[PDB]
Image (cartoon, rainbow, N blue to C red; front, side):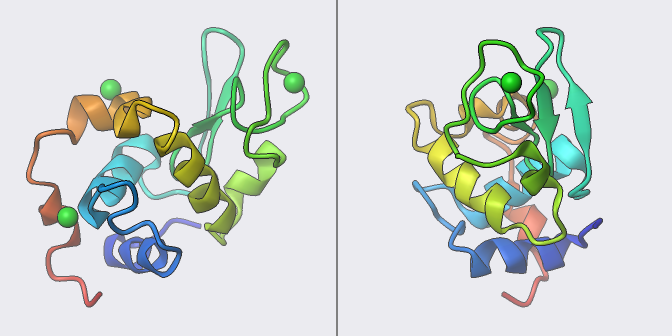
Length: 129
Ligand SMILES: [Cl-]
Ligand SMILES: [Cl-]
Ligand SMILES: [Cl-]
């Protein structure tokens, strides 16, 4: 599913991501924009052989099981395929664990490079939330 911008903001809020660990909704929408362009089915293969999955490009090295990332963990206790669903529940619940892991949203390199320090409220501007 490719979400609309406000549609995704609303879904993220519904699932308790708004201001989670102090990160406003615009941060999460911005991260999703640059990780996946709001496409739940996004996948990307990393140099180390792990894969990133879903709207927030969650990585199989630590967070989910895909059966093809040697030496990896599955800390969200989910198949990586669950992160590709039109229903963002699994991605949100896993993101909550990731952002709580110590480095906040810096876990998403894209957020650090493209969202951090910017006017992230622009991402939810106009949205009925
Ligand atoms: Cl915001
Ligand atoms: Cl594996
Ligand atoms: Cl980047």
